[PDB]
Image: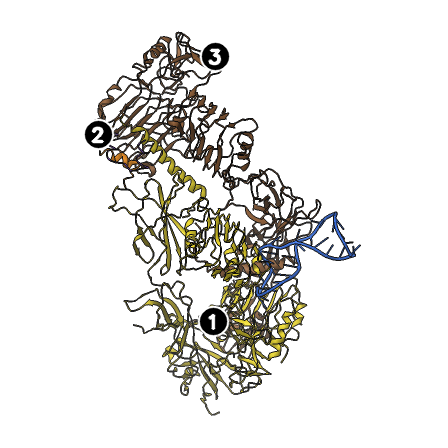
Chain colours: A orange, B purple, C yellow, D brown, E blue
Amino acid sequence: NQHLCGSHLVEALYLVCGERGFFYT
Amino acid sequence: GIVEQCCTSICSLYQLENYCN
Amino acid sequence: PGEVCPGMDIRNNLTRLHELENCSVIEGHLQILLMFKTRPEDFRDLSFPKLIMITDYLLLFRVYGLESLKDLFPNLTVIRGSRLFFNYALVIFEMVHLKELGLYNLMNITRGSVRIEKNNELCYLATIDWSRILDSVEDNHIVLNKDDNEECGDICPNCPATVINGQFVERCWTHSHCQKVCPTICKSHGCTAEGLCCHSECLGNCSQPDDPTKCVACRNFYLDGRCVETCPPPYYHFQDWRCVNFSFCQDLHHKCKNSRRQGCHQYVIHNNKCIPECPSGYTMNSSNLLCTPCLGPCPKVCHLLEGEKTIDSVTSAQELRGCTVINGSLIINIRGGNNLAAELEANLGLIEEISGYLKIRRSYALVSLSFFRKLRLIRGETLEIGNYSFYALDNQNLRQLWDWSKHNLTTTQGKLFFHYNPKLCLSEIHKMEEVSGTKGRQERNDIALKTNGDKASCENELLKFSYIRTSFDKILLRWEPYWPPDFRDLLGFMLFYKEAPYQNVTEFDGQDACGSNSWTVVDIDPPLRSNDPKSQNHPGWLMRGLKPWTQYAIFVKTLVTFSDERRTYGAKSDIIYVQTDATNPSVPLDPISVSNSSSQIILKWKPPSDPNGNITHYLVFWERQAEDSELFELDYCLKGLKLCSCPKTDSQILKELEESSFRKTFEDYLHNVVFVPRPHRPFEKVVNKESLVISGLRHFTGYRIELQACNQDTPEERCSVAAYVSARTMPEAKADDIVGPVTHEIFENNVVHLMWQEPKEPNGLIVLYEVSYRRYGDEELHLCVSRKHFALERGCRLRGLSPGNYSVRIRATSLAGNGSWTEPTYFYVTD
Amino acid sequence: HLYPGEVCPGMDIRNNLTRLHELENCSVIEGHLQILLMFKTRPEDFRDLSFPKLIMITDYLLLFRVYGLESLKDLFPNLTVIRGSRLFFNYALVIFEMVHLKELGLYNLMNITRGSVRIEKNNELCYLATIDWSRILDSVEDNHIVLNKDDNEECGDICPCPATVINGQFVERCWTHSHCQKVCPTICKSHGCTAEGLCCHSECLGNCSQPDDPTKCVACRNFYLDGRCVETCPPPYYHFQDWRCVNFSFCQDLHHKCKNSRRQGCHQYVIHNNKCIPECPSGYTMNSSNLLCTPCLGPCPKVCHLLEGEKTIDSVTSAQELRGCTVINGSLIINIRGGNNLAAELEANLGLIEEISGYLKIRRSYALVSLSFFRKLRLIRGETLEIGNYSFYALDNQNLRQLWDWSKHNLTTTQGKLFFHYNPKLCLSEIHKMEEVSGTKGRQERNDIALKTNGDKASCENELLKFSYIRTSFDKILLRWEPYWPPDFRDLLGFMLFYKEAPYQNVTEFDGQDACGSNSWTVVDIDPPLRSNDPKSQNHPGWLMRGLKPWTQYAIFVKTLVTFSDERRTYGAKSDIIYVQTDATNPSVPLDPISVSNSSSQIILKWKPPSDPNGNITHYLVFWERQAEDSELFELDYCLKGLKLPSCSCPKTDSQILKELEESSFRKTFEDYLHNVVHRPFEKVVNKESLVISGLRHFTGYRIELQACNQDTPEERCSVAAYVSARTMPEAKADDIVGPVTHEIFENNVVHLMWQEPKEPNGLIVLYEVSYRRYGDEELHLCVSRKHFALERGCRLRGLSPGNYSVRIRATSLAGNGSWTEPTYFYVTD
DNA sequence: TGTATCCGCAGTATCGGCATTCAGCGAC
């Protein structure tokens, strides 16, 4: 379906950049 | 934000590689 | 022999009881009840010796001071029972000061059963053989009398005795009149005093036998003073007990016509029957009172005033009883009522062709329009202004317009109008406009789009079940997983089921009221999303508390929260029908067993409470219970004879689906904030019956009978726990006489040996001997010879005997009765 | 001693564990501490990282999805106060999606000053129900502790804090497995408390070192100044961040430090009223050198220039960014989803704005009761509008009831059209009063304000009806009220009449919600009467209620039903509720009467009060009567055949209704026929349930009947009777005979015997049993009954052997047997 | 000096009727 919502997106956008890590100001 | 452009519309891998480093 | 009075109802005074002074056969029900201020001395000079026959029933409830009923109705013979009081043809209830029944002449309660309950002094109830009176003895309810303890002295006058359930006791109504029993060669016709049989056409009794013109209660029909099998032309049967000519049935008509039609039955003539009202598919003529066939359900026809008939409440709907077409229109507007789904359907659930406009404005208590059971055409020759032909605004509870799987409805002219209906959704209107023919022959409807179909959902998808595995008591069932595009919107599944033995049940049926339900609802939590369409995840439920072999109707619907656009998702599956399996039944209830000969038992029982399937047959075993051997050791001439709740209200549902969106908004705020982008015994098998005539038996030997009810036979049959009952056979009379002359032996010291031989086939046991020596001209002294004395001595040693000739009578008392005395045993010495 | 470290700015730690290296030298943290999103960690790393010397966290603490943290004890073993000056969606402590967390561990936390706590979606959390948050927070009802592993009792919950009774149970309170939640006595409420039971100085919190000293505690309360902490810090110093006091060199350093406008972080800190505030409010302006702000030259507001063209308000952390603003330069959309009640922290934050410039869309708010938090709103200009030229837009508010108080308020909308849909508790008078008061009067299109969907669950009328004649009977009740007509008499659809039963007069007024479940008003409808074209006529309508049970209190009221339209009239009228009770009838039958015999004189009897008393039962009434024995037991020979010896909804099939139909049919045959119809030793038994009767004849039978009875001395009216047959227990020495029996000798060897019949038996002597005995044989006996005893005058013996025979004589009654006599010898010699 | 709103019950209850009862204007 790829309407990723809820905990689905926080588990599924770790997997796209699991080596670098998240970004903030 | 991210839930507004990824739970009311579809998202590409380029659009959600924008959120980390 | 007398007049034919009608049915009365006497209460609170005895003066109305004088109106039975002259009548003989009552063409009605007799009912004496509720007399408080009555003295018991006001019943000695009160007697009705002419009452012969009652045709409806007899009820006798709480008459203070009535001692016995044998001085009040001394000549009842036939209670017909063409009409009954709760399937009870004789009710005697809460009657105090009543000692015995004493109706010593009634011979045949034709159709029904007796109920005698809650009396405080009613003796003489265990000495009445109801199976010689009640032709259906199985279902009389006789409890809580004086005889709840074995206490009352029901002594008896020489009067014949028969077995009922083993207890071989005597039969009598009172202590002065016993039950008139007849041999079974005169089954219901009634025999005279000598025992020779009567004519084969009258019932109960007859004054002189073999003549049908002198009988006192006729069973088939009574014509011109005589019994008649079936009445000749041109007579008509009337109330199925007598026969009248044309002028009586006819005359009766104007009788009612002239009486406000208030308490009379307009009698019509049909198939030589004076019928109260002739049934459907038939019309009454007005010339000669016959009832003529009409093709199909024939029109009323039903005109009305000024074209408009505002149906305010159900009483306004009482003018349309059985109309077929309407030469006008209809405007229904109902707000409240009780049992409204039944009353409106019974009133106007037969209307077919409306020749105007239908209009359902402001009906608040209408949940569905399904009570128009036979509506087929709305012609529309008079339209509502604006050219409308189905006008519908402001129906607060309308949900279901019709059942569009099994219906058809043509509006030949006019348009539609559907405004301000909250619960009625767009799918029913869009289905009606293409099943009636108004989107064709194109005619512009005026249907608002935003104010139809709120607080509900009808743009749904559909679920599909996948695994229905049934058992004898439980059913587990699983369906496809469902996920809305934002997967936290789904709150849970709701599963409705209801027992339905037919296949016409739909969703919104049975409530017809405020928020009620006839279904049974359970809730299912949503499953776990394993982020994969191919997983073992799809939910299901296990219904437990069911009944075997029935048809259940089952469907399931989701419970999603409202999106912030007024867009409700969800899916309700189709109504499915499932059937549980079979199970071995319960025991056959209350078996009874009366005998009628020396080697026969008949049985009567009931079919079981829960059959749990089509019962194919029964099974019955009988075994012998020989003799109670501990009865062998009693001297009988000393004293006598030894023998979970879950309601879901509006406030709870709204609180639940508000909290289940508050949590979603908090984690949506969290995901917005934290993510920043970058720039053995024999047997018998009886089928489809409730009786059995056993044969080939020993006389007066108690049998034990086991009963089985067995539903499936061919694939390795199974059935129930056996029901146990006992039975006895009526003994033969001849088999107790002493065979041969009784031998005397004279010893010198004035003790004599009187020996005899026991009869070669007794009935049960021979318990005592009565020997009687007497000098002719002198008194008699009785001697009881015990079983033990005869067993030790092989005779009797009679002490205290002066010399001389003596007449000696010998008898042997068994468990049945007396046999006969022997010859006078003369041992003589010449003086 | 108080704070031995360094005041620390707000931090944010993610994606590693090295960034915690700057948390070893911070005792207070101005700002917030978020530790979140560490996916690849192991529990071996957290055991040797400990921050033992932080005390005060001023804003909040968010731990969202940190893997490898099992206990929170060794991380923060010393934080006492979470102040909560800038919250996070009303919550000052958010523990979210901690997967590896076992215990809460925060054993030294005392005071959460402002805010609540939300602990949600943990899979392995326990020791959660033994914390007593009511001694930690100051407001408990806004918490959210839901969806943990403590939904089911499976995680221990054993611990060795005097087991408070703040709920209806007796539960111990404990943070961890080896620590308990520190509770001390309440002679000082929350003023700091030392462990051994002595209260320390009042201006401190939590732990203390020595009592009655405000110089050596650990967490002050009001402010803090250089070792001590006083209530009002002296004016060589100024207030700062509402917890410190600093001199003006520091505020000047901050101002001249971040006046270099290269970043968007700080504020231009000014001094005002001894407060180093970020910006002093409207009506003030800052001189450059002095750093204070003086009153403004005339009136000047603080324009709150809104980002992105609109602002949505969800909670406290979004309503705190409009703090002190006066005019808003953009639209404001109020949306408070879910919630319990939030009208207390909105009024102190956004209850000072005066001119919004866009619209005020109020949608989906569930916990809103009134808009009274908009305290000083006056002008809605509407330069930017909504889709369709709207300025006030209320849509789907489940609990809105009152917009303002129009007796003491003013509001002007310049342009645009107002909109009102789905407000199902809001009366129609409020929006029409708003159209009257405000500037918009005729700028509507039909239909914009939905006249049908508002106020349908709130009965809202202004006129009232009065009842003129209330007649009362025992079954039916009569009503007749005063006529009512709207100014257009063709606009009336009829009355509605609600009635219910309630024995207690504390019935609340009707709330609009038509009750339907179990406790509900029954509603009937009345058609409107016929127009009589005259003032004084038959215009009084009426009604007659028929199915009512006698002697109970009924609460009734009436209401009208009219059709709304464009004219602001025909609201309707509604009477106040009244209470009428019906009359009393004859009562029911006394239920379940049992008679129990114990001795030869006592008989006890009990029953139950009837099912339908129909009034307060005054007294019962018991009559009894001596039945005599059967005369047919007097003239029979009784050693023939026969001897006497007296003494969830569970929905099933409703096809069983016919037996109860029989019983209720005879009960209604009582009632429908008793609408028309109204020496013996007795006693007026009053206020009892059992009865003893002593001192009567033995073994005889009595018929007894009992009635219940209501009010007595004027016109005695009791029910129908109930009948019981009773029999007492027998006596021992009644049928036994004493005295010498006498034998008489006849010449024809028929021997006569004389005895006495017993003078009183237990009921009736029925047989005499004489037996004679010799030595060697058994006893041979003989029947004799009353007729043979009378006609033989004793008993005669026929034809026995000569010698000496012993005689033994019994008597048996219908109750049983008696004993023998002395064996007397009768002898003949030959 | 009488006359005069039923709404859904009454029950062996079919088609059109009447219970329930405090009241003073309108002709007769």
Look at the image and tell me whether residue D602 can be seen: no
Which quarter of the picture shows residue C608?
bottom left
Is disc 3 placed on a helix, strand or loop?
A: loop
| Residue C270 x/y as whole percent | 54, 76
Say above or below: C211 vs D33: below
Say above or below: C508 vs C730: above
| Residue D516 x/y as whole percent | 50, 46
Identify the subunit bearing mark 1.
Answer: C
Residue most extreme to the bottom: C830
Residue most extreme to the left: A19
Is disc 1 placed on a helix, strand or loop?
A: helix
The type of residue carrying mark 3 is Leu
Say above or below: D744 vs C322: below
Q: On the picture, is D633 further left or further right than C486?
A: right
Frontmost residue, D401 versus D555: D401
Give the total of numbered labels: 3
Identify the subunit bearing mark 3.
Answer: D
Q: CA distance from mark 3 to mark 2?
A: 61 Å
What's the mark number on residue D41? 2
Between label 3 and label 2, give the one nearer the viewer: 3
Say above or below: C232 vs D793: below
Mark 3 burial class by Cα count in 10 Å: few <14, some 14-19, many 20+: few
The type of residue carrying mark 2 is Thr
Q: Quadrant of the N terminus of chain D?
A: top left
Q: CA distance from mark 2 to mark 1?
A: 87 Å
Query: Where does label 3 land, which residue?
Result: D297
| Residue C725 x/y as whole percent | 39, 69
Q: Are marks 3 and 2 on the same chain?
A: yes
Query: Where does label 1 land, which residue?
Result: C137
